[PDB]
Image: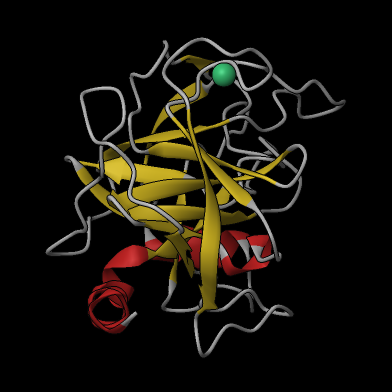
Length: 223
Ligand SMILES: [Ca+2]
């Protein structure tokens, strides 16, 4: 997250870190046994880390649970990042309390202009590299589909939306991928891609979760 703020320990209780010896992506807990992330975060043999604030220090609310199964969306295209969504099942159920909690799936798609909370452990610099240890947060609006497509001609599908600031300065970034965009208390987006970070007229691009609720629910119901 570039231009954000320190969230506070366990203030984003559905935020998880995907760990394969090191943090490499975010994700969102959507029930006690399932995490939703980006398909471009796929890799074998990872551990899901819940209850994290400082990802390099054991602070006493962590739950570490290995993944039993990954399911990349059946139509994921890594060249275009169309359908950049994946489900991760945990080997055991997380224990849910105020500091570890699931985030509700949307019942409708959030409109441009809705303010949302974006969070992750990704890069905090737009020209340079500095990775934070504690979770960072950004409050940012969904941008119109027209400004999204004008910023990224030929690249925005109906499974994507833009959020952030066309003037730059505030954005998600590398290492935030797979993490949440939460609006009015529901999971509306997944940190997916963008050109650089916090650049002018290159806002963040997010997987449009509301398109995938039927697939998520049916998948969870059979796996
Ligand atoms: Ca920790």
